[PDB]
Amino acid sequence: LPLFHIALLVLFMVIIYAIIGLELFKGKMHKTCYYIGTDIVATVENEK
Amino acid sequence: QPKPIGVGIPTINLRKRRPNVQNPKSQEPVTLDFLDAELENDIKVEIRN
View 1 (tube, chains in turn yellow, green):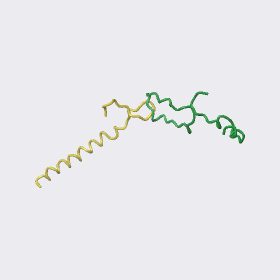
View 2 (view 1 turned 90 degrees about the vertical axis):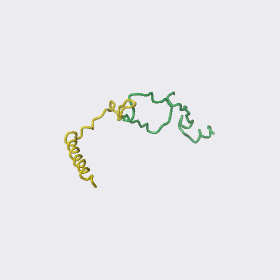
View 3 (view 1 turned 45 degrees about the vertical axis):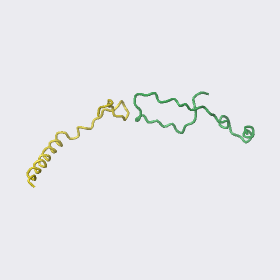
View 4 (view 1 turned 135 degrees about the vertical axis):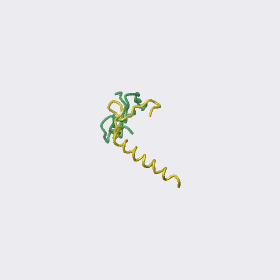
């Protein structure tokens, strides 16, 4: 019970840092590294 | 006539392959039926049997 002045910070700090991410980074993650005309992702053995 | 036999409709997608590996060459024999090497007839089946 002496932590809901501290846990209320991160929950307000997430809501701050979620919306900043959602404005700046909206939908950047979609472009591919596929092959020539096919449907395989192109990675190198260890790479995500 | 070389060129082995007998498949359904030969479906290939080109979305699945890679610009790569050799795609095996079918160790399948060429076993042609006599009733499919020619026209089928009531006389020839008597000959074949």
